[PDB]
Length: 40
Length: 48
Length: 48
Length: 49
Ligand SMILES: *[C@@H]1O[C@H](CO)[C@@H](O[C@@H]2O[C@H](CO)[C@@H](O[C@@H]3O[C@H](CO)[C@@H](O)[C@H](O)[C@@H]3O)[C@H](O)[C@H]2NC(C)=O)[C@H](O)[C@H]1NC(C)=O
Ligand SMILES: *[C@@H]1O[C@H](CO)[C@@H](O)[C@H](O)[C@H]1NC(C)=O
Ligand SMILES: *[C@@H]1O[C@H](CO)[C@@H](O)[C@H](O)[C@H]1NC(C)=O
Image (tube, rainbow over all chains, first blue to last red; front, side, top):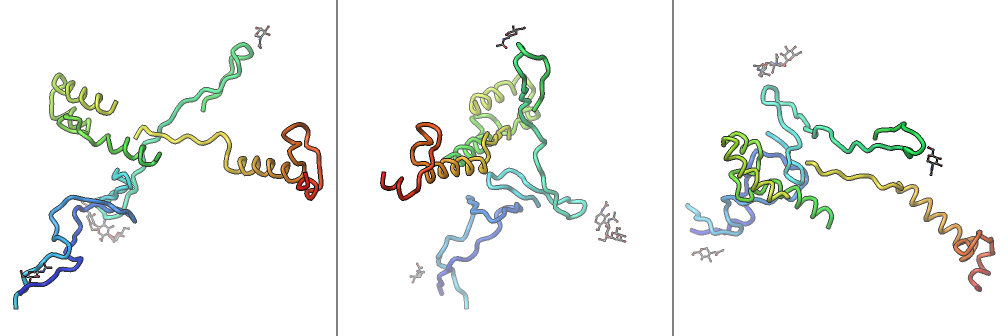
């Protein structure tokens, strides 16, 4: 089967702490609203 | 393990020997301005 | 405008300008000084 | 990182005092405090001018 991965699978890209700030990064991520393989 | 500021310079670290947080401030620096009256009046000066 | 220009001026410290690093201590330890002169010259030229 | 921000010569309080001076003159004395020594005048009459 297939399913829409709404807004999910983001993770901490580094062990840095950043406080109340809109940081931006390039990394391997699950694309937003991608199409996940659902197994029964 | 360590904090960054808005400009992504290091702002804090966790001490790996004992896990408290150390804030890191720059070593202090600045201009040595000299205040003087006219040398055509005194040789006394003050340092800012 | 001033914050963007200041943060740009700071971020430009981390740019390599075709040197082997943007961190001056790396250049002062990954090379002998007679080669490191060129790498520092690139960083000086870029920062300047 | 070698960057420094220096203070203004006048503090925000002093600017608030100067703008209050400018205003207190403008209220009590018309344009006269620009042109010379401040001359008091009743505010309704400054408006009639
Ligand atoms: C690495 O971490 C350990 C675990 O913290 C350090 O050993 C000691 O562990 C205890 C429990 O975590 C710490 O808490 C308490 O400290 C007070 C100090 O007044 C003491 O009265 C208590 O009996 C209890 O020990 C303790 O602070 C912590 N540190 C020391 C120096 O005892 C360990 O020391 C660290 N590694 C190295 C190589 O030091
Ligand atoms: C996900 O893939 C299935 C099969 O290709 C398709 O039916 C569905 O429309 C796709 N969904 C999205 C969000 O593209
Ligand atoms: C400069 O100093 C001399 C004395 O050394 C004095 O005669 C002169 O008036 C001074 N000028 C000013 C502008 O202070």
